[PDB]
Image 1 (tube, each protein chain N blue to C red):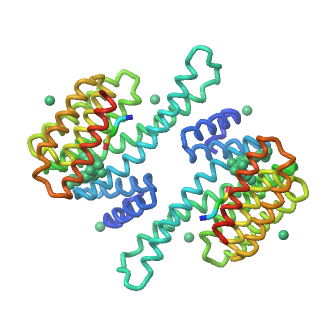
Image 2: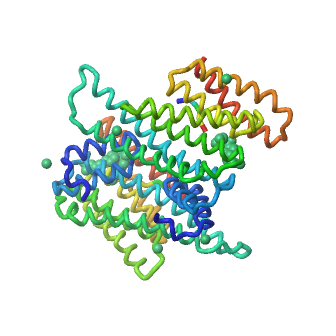
Length: 236
Length: 236
Length: 5
Length: 5
Ligand SMILES: *CC(=O)NCCCC1CCN(C(=O)C(C)(C)Oc2ccc(Cl)cc2)CC1
Ligand SMILES: *CC(=O)NCCCC1CCN(C(=O)C(C)(C)Oc2ccc(Cl)cc2)CC1
Ligand SMILES: [Mg+2]
Ligand SMILES: [Mg+2]
Ligand SMILES: [Mg+2]
Ligand SMILES: [Mg+2]
Ligand SMILES: [Mg+2]
Ligand SMILES: [Mg+2]
């Protein structure tokens, strides 16, 4: 890889610079290089990895949605034939998105997950696996769509099982996992009741544990709890 | 080039899609492909070309400024030595920015400018030449900095001379040229009085010609006049 | 779109 | 930064 010659610490330093400069493609490439050094990641380094790829794929998803909407409108009755260009360009963006997802999944499989023994790290990586399979599922239309959806579900479920056994109900990683798995249920698995149930139970169990927290931990937990509430409001 | 196999009309279509998706790197690559077909550009196509590259280089300039500020702070007294990484990454962004500028200048030189005979097209392309030399000048620190600054000045001046002879004082291309040349004076050439004089005279001569315009032309001209006023306010 | 982190 | 177009 192109980052093979750069020191691990320098890659991390530059990922932080790239973040400050809002250069998320660079940030992701630096963090990929750092992962490929083969050492486990710290908490901060996991955050850098996730922020980088979330921002890159987030942009791709937004672009894909714009293009897919234009494509859908083109295939309505009364729409003038404009040739293959809309489909082609949607496919181009789609293929790039799939590439980034495959890259992230590859880092998780080689070898982040298998070396992650602490609950926080294992849950975080399994959540990421669920997330990137979910992004693949958003654009899937073929023979494998069901298996892609099930790959997302399986990763999220393993993360949920560990999180419930090993982490308090206010832990931000546990909360974020539940938020995202709930969205998976609503948007991907066609299970809006399960989505709502998950978000509500997660919110309520966190509420009951806030009394145990410092001011700073309270801030962190309540921020994600508000996201759960926001989704519940959208869905009910 | 990678766009050599795509129809000119399809490249233009896809540039418009890329704009809608806020995919400005793609938009620029499509427009580069379209220019390289060798035919002159229409007014709309000139706009697409300029929008694409303005957005790509704009992002690079913003990133470069973030990194240069961090680098400058690192070289103050009391700042802890952090190694070569800040300089390296600023250089990386800088080299990419210079590459995009060189690409645009290359399209102008081969062969957009030489084929542009109408005042609007020739002024537009010469303005672009001034702009991309100005971006090169922003990051220049070496033997060639003076020649880069003079290249920008020369292009802007040729555009100004044509614009004054051939276009009304409210023409948006004439106005935009003057706005940018004024910024060149203030930020690049260390000539703030010339910047102010240019912006003021341009504003005043446009004001006097608004009476000739339709409602729609008035809207277009007054928008750029407000930018001149905004700069004057910043500078006085 | 719903919130995710 | 000043306005340019
Ligand atoms: C110790 C460890 O493994 N830490 C990994 C990073 C956990 C951070 C991520 C950022 N946090 C957040 O609350 C926000 C909302 C900013 O983003 C999240 C991203 C991912 C998850 Cl799983 C939760 C939250 C704090 C915890
Ligand atoms: C006929 C022709 O050659 N047209 C080229 C495009 C001229 C457009 C550009 C967009 N316009 C603007 O007023 C704004 C402010 C959006 O941007 C500009 C960009 C570049 C210039 Cl030179 C002026 C304005 C209208 C004129
Ligand atoms: Mg080493
Ligand atoms: Mg496809
Ligand atoms: Mg349950
Ligand atoms: Mg042809
Ligand atoms: Mg350099
Ligand atoms: Mg004068």
